[PDB]
Length: 286
Length: 152
Length: 110
Image 1 (cartoon, each protein chain N blue to C red):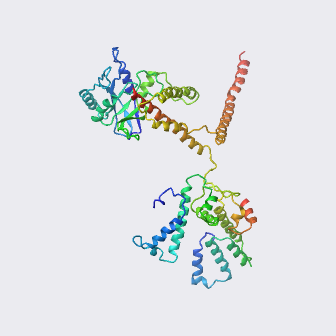
Image 2: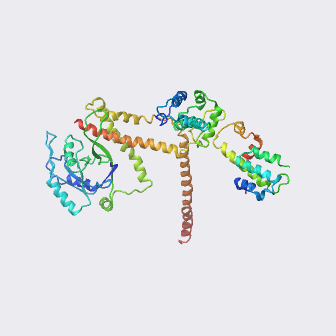
Image 3: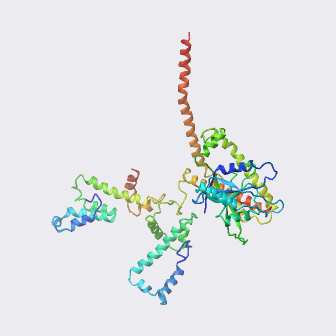
């Protein structure tokens, strides 16, 4: 149904406010906020959101506390001031997906339309993208397990339309723009290996742990496609790609001729002014 | 109809000879088969151009697969002369066979292995393979990472 | 009018009773040229250039244009049979036209 979503940083800075208005009490649980957006178009666009007092139990996980009057009053007044945005779903700040999320999401599945779920981290130490759109749809399983709520990962992007780019750029004054060239390219080409190294290294360790020490079926069926796609590149002998290395290396030669020739053109004004300025300033100094 | 639908397996028409014969013999259904063969030459054109039409259509089906069926051996399995196979190639030159490769020494044909420009063909294949491995690797990795959360 | 590859109007001009009374040995060679053009044959056109060369010997300078039509149909045949054949025998492809490889090789290489 929905291919991609658009999440503005305003809601995540509202999660910064979720971490600001705590009051130093010692709970810091998965505070659930009422996510708002535009479900009209096929693409989802989050503009702003708000929160609702949400408290769980220490031992029992099935305890969840929501509010209907606060949702209808905040949504009623928010719709009165801005009717272009309506309820879409919710989101929790907890890093782990608990079992009670089917009951928490089930309320906004009954009263509200199909709600999207977003899992983020309480500490911004994760290098990866903090936002993951999880659609709440029921899927048929091939093994015969009963139909239940399944959270499929929907791709997400963090973009601002008109003003939040200006506000973020003015508040930071440290981040740089695209700036195609040497630095913005070589930084990605340096740290990219760590950007994949922390993800893969962080995932395959617990993966290999759950291979031998795993039960409660983790959908082992998708592991066959995992190792299949991993074995779709069986160390090609590079025999056919030699001519492609001749093409890319020939373009490399083109960049060699462009650099040497163009820089040789740049040497004109320098290697002329260095003489005509020094000898004339010297002969005319005294 | 199911054999003529798609994925036409290379089979002998001798099994269809008795099927068409009994198709002319039985009168319970499709009775006007003798009316199909009413004219002395029209039915012969429908039959020769029919077997020709399926013996070209199966070539158009196996032409999608690059398995290199080695039509020199296929002419032996079909039990027909290579001259009317050259006439079949005379039907392929008007059937847009321009994307093919022939051999002067041998008789094996090639429906693939073009000049293969690395900036277009290997570019496209490497794009779909590498990118497909990247995003496909991206989906079930974190998806399974969410599947293992329910075990706690 | 035969230079623009339309033999049907040639048949229309040799079938009319008006120009039929002026027919003779001259228009027969043109009927063979139009027949070879509508048949898309080459050795038949060489037969028209062989039997009628005793009315094609007094032919005007347009003989170069007729040779341009001969070489034009030859070009059509060459781009017809060679185009699907990447690598094929010269006798397997020249046997269809049953002509020597000397003139064909010279025109091709040219």
